[PDB]
Image (cartoon, rainbow, N blue to C red; front, side, top):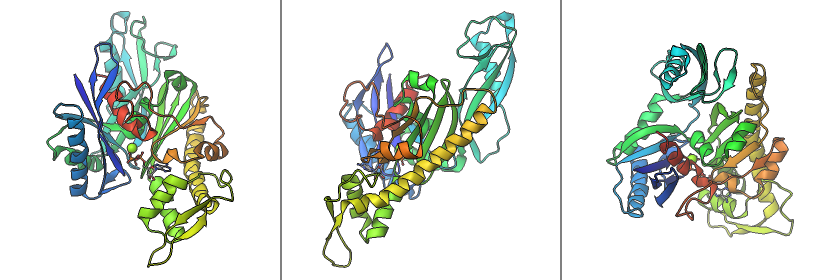
Length: 382
Ligand SMILES: Nc1ncnc2c1ncn2[C@@H]1O[C@H](COP(=O)(O)OP(=O)(O)OP(=O)(O)O)[C@@H](O)[C@H]1O
Ligand SMILES: [Mg+2]
């Protein structure tokens, strides 16, 4: 009937509500945003401050939709998120692969020993195989005698998840499921065509770099880094002697990811501390600090793609991501990301926004909303 998201981000908390229409298309009924205090690297850092932030967005969203919120789908990220790939097996009773046969094979590959510190988050079947026929998708009706699956397992640190759950539960809400941020950030920015050719998505944000790699129409790997937009924000402050509050504004209003797209005759007013006059500083100099960090950040994604690409072809599956890299999130909005990305990467870079948003489209237009609407796409499926 009604579905609710909750992207508890490192900087802003987004909360969307929508209703499932009979055909399937979900239209958004109400949005909600609020700055988040007490957050760092996608994890909880001050429990009482994030609880107030979650209530700020959930109350304004319950009001913009004329309905009471009771259950939510929440996102989750952090360096602790890890991915595993495990194979399984199963018999095909009465030579027809019924759905009861399909979950048994998944159950076998899913049942492993991980420990208590690890919490299972996603079990994503990649490519099936049915008697010398490999790489089949949805074989619901293929006559065979036995089948093996290659499930993709997403796991996260359990304790860091309990904190996020505790925050939402203290507002009278019930959590439905935890969702990896980059997975939702990919479900709402990608077209099915791009998935099959091969793509790399990255939720560039305040404190998290949520990477998801897709080849052959299946999620292959997921990795997260803790250096994000808050790193370049600090670099501006620490290099010019300007307060963090002011250094953020200079980043959003005059920041450039390449120190050659800005003209020498451009200047910015960077303030000072102590009671000093605000100096007028070259706009090129500002971009000269943002450029090295973005290159290093994308260098981590490049090193991740290469390590996944190597171990991918070495096992016999689609390895080269054709559609390229898709950038999203807040810190992907700076002028010149596609230019500095195309230098460190050598694949198709774009700054994809949420797609096919229905109704109330003015609040789900910018890429920093992708993770939020992606929670709706995931919740739409059951
Ligand atoms: N125009 C802009 N140019 C450069 N950076 C920007 C711009 N607008 C926003 N940002 C950066 O985007 C970041 C916020 O990202 P975003 O809102 O997507 O994160 P979030 O949802 O709060 O959390 P998460 O860390 O989990 O992605 C901030 O670090 C901010 O500096
Ligand atoms: Mg986010």
